[PDB]
Amino acid sequence: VPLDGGRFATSDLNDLYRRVINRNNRLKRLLDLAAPDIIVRNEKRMLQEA
Amino acid sequence: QSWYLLYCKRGQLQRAQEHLERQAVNCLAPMITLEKIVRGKRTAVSEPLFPNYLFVEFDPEVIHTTTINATRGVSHFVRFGASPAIVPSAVIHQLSVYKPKDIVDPATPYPGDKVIITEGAFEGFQAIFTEPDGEARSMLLLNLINKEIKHSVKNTEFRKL
Amino acid sequence: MGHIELASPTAHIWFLKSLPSRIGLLLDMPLRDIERVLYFESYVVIEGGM
DNA sequence: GGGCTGCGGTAGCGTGACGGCGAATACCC
DNA sequence: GGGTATTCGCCGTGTACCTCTCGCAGCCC
RNA sequence: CCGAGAGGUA
């Protein structure tokens, strides 16, 4: 919901879900494009930590 | 020397690459020319096939990992733990010749596909590509509840499904 | 509710770091080596065999 | 103009709570 | 081979109300 | 109409 102005008082949960979905979409694209071992390792690592 | 992997900031691989070219650090990033809608204009941009990832070859004695970590445009080394990761020479060798398949293009529309409209008096209408005019705009077979129409529009007022 | 299909599976961190770790003393395995497996700096065998 | 994204930088910032408790491990067998 | 003994990192630290300001900067896509 | 920071009454 917005506070009184032109900007939304954002919530922390939507930041967390947006971070998880962005990392998961990047990981799907890298598993599709057959990235090397260390790149998809880092991608799954950042997904785990997110 | 050896090879390390750097994750960079989003959309600053070029700037970090320019700083590491001003330094003595050999970079490597598989660039593929992907046809991407920038601002309404289908511009083929030689963008990285990977995300913000980048490869460097240096030795820690010559230029230190702290100095590489503090480079303008670099987020961090890929670590997995304490030390930054070593990629083996086979990965660098097999990422010399690569990028075979296509101009794959996530989220930019190819013609002969199905889209949606994002603004205007046709917002919410699924459309078929008949024939875009080139690399500048597109032409769309828009649906209605009675009869389909067609229109020559720029690439900001519609997006792919 | 809804869901997100993770392209790689993910250890739930409550069951990993509840102290004592449920995964830890379930696998008869120390928490340090489990985090070394999960955060992608060690391998652990499955069906070593011969 | 705006979608995104988490230190800004070719390092270093942190520094003035305190107790209890239970597990993880160090030292010495 | 386990039996202490030290370290470490997790928990926790009053209630109710009232007022005020301030709440993304940068940016290279 | 949610969070942070500062102050106050009991």
Image (cartoon, coloured by chain):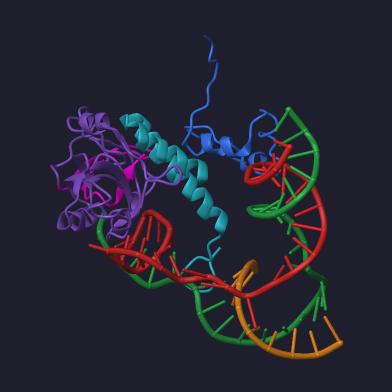
Chain colours: A cyan, B purple, C blue, D red, E green, F orange
Q: Is residue D3 left or right of residue C6?
A: left
**Magenta span includes B137:** yes
Quadrant in the rendering for residue A22: top left
Which quarter shows the N terminus of chain A? Answer: bottom right
Instruction: Judge whether residue B157 can be spotted in this image.
Output: yes
Looking at this view, name the residue that lies furthest to the top. C50
Is C30 left, or right, of B149 in this rendering?
right
Measuring 41% from the left and 40% from the top, which residue is drawn there? A42
Rendered view: C25 above or below B7 = above
Residue B69's spot in the image, x, y percent?
32, 56
Give the number of marks. Answer: 0
The magenta span reads: B136-161
The picture places residue B47, in percent across and down from the top left corner, at: 21, 45
Q: On screen, C24 above or below F5?
A: above
The x, y position of residue D28, in whole percent, is 70, 43
* Residue C17 horizontal/vertical position (percent): 65, 43
Residue at the image position 22 percent from the left and 29 percent from the top: B94
Task: Look at the picture and state if B126 lies above or below C43.
Answer: below
